[PDB]
Length: 49
Length: 40
Length: 50
Length: 49
Ligand SMILES: *[C@@H]1O[C@H](CO)[C@@H](O)[C@H](O)[C@H]1NC(C)=O
Image (tube, rainbow over all chains, first blue to last red; front, side):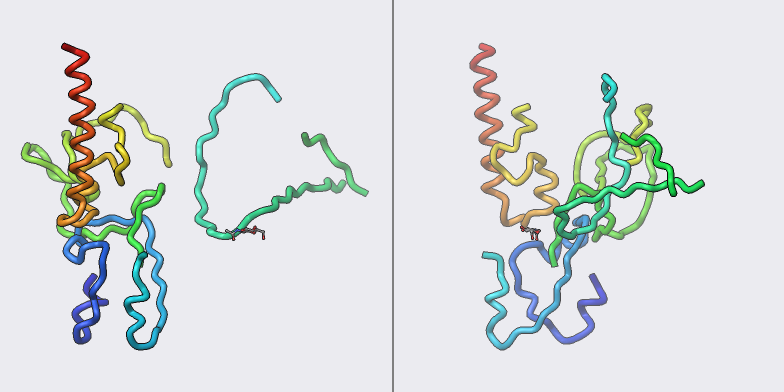
C-alpha cells in the first residue's frame, strides 16, 4: 500500500467501495488485479452498476 | 458397498479456476500380454 | 482490484503493524482485523489441518 | 438462532461490518439488524410474560 502510491504525482483515486483509510485493517483471501487502458472520459464507465 | 458411516474430510483444495465438464479414469495393466487384477 | 474473502483463510492482510503475542492484561482484543470478545486460553479440542 | 440470523443483511457480525463497510455507510444495515433483534426479543418477552 506504499509502493503503488506516493511515488508519482497524484492519481485519479476517486472510487466508491473500500475506504482508503480502511486499507490498513482489512483482510482479503484473494485479489484479482486486471490492467487496461481507455480513452478520455471513459473512467466513469468503469464503475459498479 | 459396505454398510457403515464414514465421513470424508477435505484433504486439499485446488484453486484451478478452469471449466471442467467431463472426467476420465485411468487404469494399469500388470506386466510379468498383460494381466488385469480385480478393480471395482 | 477486488478485495473479497473466500472459504480459504486470508493469506494476504493489509494490517502489518507491530507483531506481538503478549498477554496477562485485560482490556480488549482484536483478531484478524475483526473485533470480538473472549480471552485466548488453551484449547483441548484438536483442530483438523484444514 | 435469531441472534445468529442475518435478517436479510450482508452479515450477522457487526464487527466485520465495521471493519469492512464504510463508516458513513452501513447505518441502515445495522439499524435493520438491531430492529430485527428488537422484534425478536420483544416477541420473546411477550411470550415469556
Ligand atoms: C463450460 O463449458 C460448457 C460447454 O462448453 C458451457 O456450457 C459452460 O457455460 C462453460 N462454463 C464456463 C464457466 O465457462
